[PDB]
Image 1 (cartoon, rainbow, N blue to C red):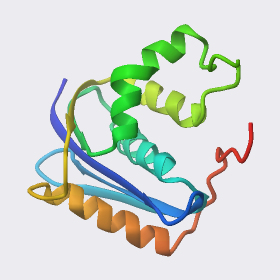
Image 2: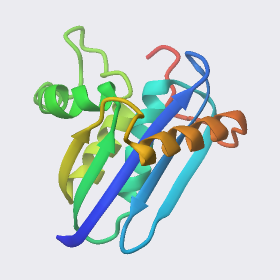
Image 3: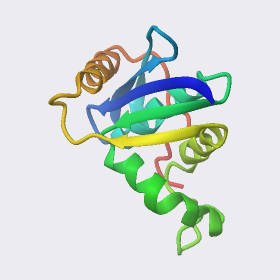
Length: 155
């Protein structure tokens, strides 16, 4: 609904797992907001999901969103996986909980209430805002403050 919002997200992690962080830019109105935080022990896929979550949870009113991310992970979950996982109760064929279910659900919630146009960007070239999110992500990763509580070592 809300006029029009553009979101740019990225995530980056130094180990699997390792320190990681995210960067999200929100062009909410005729201005910009930036979100960026670094985690002590996490994964790159977790940081790519967290980036879209934080930005989307920042929106109060129902909006028409244009979210731009180069994340193959997010891309696959959104267009392939999610509808399928729900049908199966968020469990794989071996009945274990889907990996990063905590984040997938949190993202699924934040989705719900918006009209989103998803733009799947290829590379940093010609995508300045995405390159900047990467930079923020990398800086936060170097100065981690928070712990990633959903990070499952096993299951």
